[PDB]
Amino acid sequence: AAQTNAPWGLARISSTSPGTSTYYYDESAGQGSCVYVIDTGIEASHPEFEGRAQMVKTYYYSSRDGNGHGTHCAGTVGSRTYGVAKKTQLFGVKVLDDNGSGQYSTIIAGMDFVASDKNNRNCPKGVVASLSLGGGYSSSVNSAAARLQSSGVMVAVAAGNNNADARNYSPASEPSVCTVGASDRYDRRSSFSNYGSVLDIFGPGTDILSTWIGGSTRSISGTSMATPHVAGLAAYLMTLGKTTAASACRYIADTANKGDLSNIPFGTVNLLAYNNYQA
Image 1 (tube, helix red, strand yellow):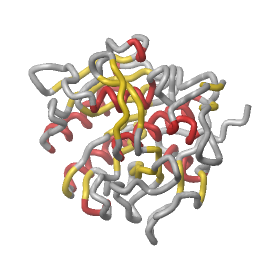
Image 2 (tube, one colour; image 1 turned 180 degrees about the horizontal axis):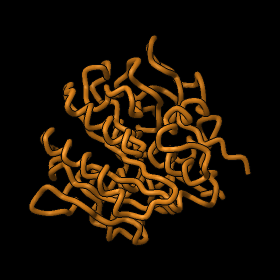
Image 3 (cartoon, one colour; image 1 turned 90 degrees about the vertical axis):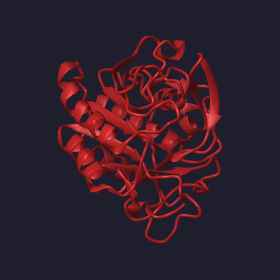
């Protein structure tokens, strides 16, 4: 398939060179897979989700996305115009309030919930989880992320927006989950993106147009926007049978565009998410 005039991030992960405007991808588009978006929620009512999004857990007086952040990430995973896995199923776990804040004990609870709740859902091509969130170092948070990975779920987490080493943030610093850095449309490391040996892969994360609450759309920036590209990609590759939940992050790194990013510090991988689709 080809999406003409796609967002630059979608075109990037299906291209070998920056500057293109078409997203090339297999028509399966993630059908049969499931991506849990652990964030401020999702506006499942958005016509861009085509009824494929549904909230399954909240920890606040409401399960609605009063922020847009979670709706923006979910649209990059699987929205029809802005997503990587356009036929995937999106589940919303609202661990963050409408300021984008959330306590560690709640985020942990959310992750434990996803490990259990995938057993209630039909996902014959596997399960992905996208955690566009984090904070200071916490081993309990890291264990939580590793528990989720070990239970059969592909975990992708943002590396952080502190332009520092991700060793000091969580769950970004958990070795067994996929930790995603951010790049821009010119293959530069995003000015804000964290770095460090704990990174596994980079995805598009500067000026990312995607869905927004109110049935709208906007462009924003962060390793929060890079994470759902890789999560979408994981789910896309899993539907195709090329990798598994346990093996996807390694697969994405093996098959990534190598050595094409600028400003990548010494010790940080130089790998850009890439779907190697050959029509």
